[PDB]
Amino acid sequence: SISISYSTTYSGWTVADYLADWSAYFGDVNHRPGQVVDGSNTGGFNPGPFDGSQYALKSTASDAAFIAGGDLHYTLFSNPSHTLWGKLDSIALGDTLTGGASSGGYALDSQEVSFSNLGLDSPIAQGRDGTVHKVVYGLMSGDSSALQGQIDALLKAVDPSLSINSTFDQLAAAGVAHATPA
Ligand code: NA
Image (cartoon, rainbow, N blue to C red; front, side, top):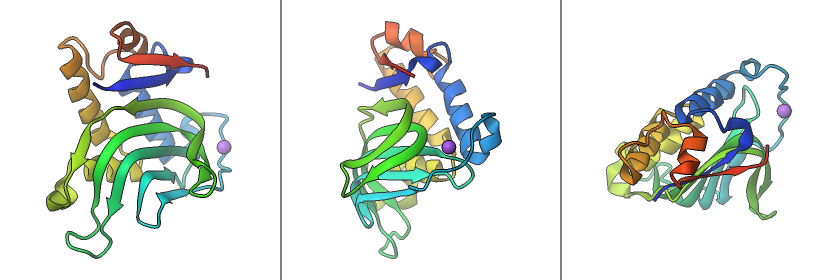
């Protein structure tokens, strides 16, 4: 079942509220007053160049960033072309990337929220219709709608009462989520 780690900054926020804010910040640094854009590490595949156990990316408009973990692949020109597929175990969201393939993998300088044990596995046959593609390609432009829908489904699988409108603290009571320092 889904496991969620969250900075205590977000304890009283709902999952939907948090994803909306991260996505808005991905589109515009000004969404979070006080932040400046000064990240140099923009991510990529680890090990890469186009497959890895991680795919990390930083926004161009802000230092909002994410890291997808699992066993991931990008088809390039191979049919079905421009497809991101494979096993997606985790999505971590936050601000600024550090590391890389030769430095212990990618990490977030400030990890805000992580969603793990996602259990997503999209075969190459589905192409750009696969859920892994929709989730990770969406996040590449800061769009968290596909991710959100998968989190909602996974929460409802734990208990009918849980959803993306639950707070992180409510999800912690349910046994799904765990707080981290800010
Ligand atoms: Na910054």
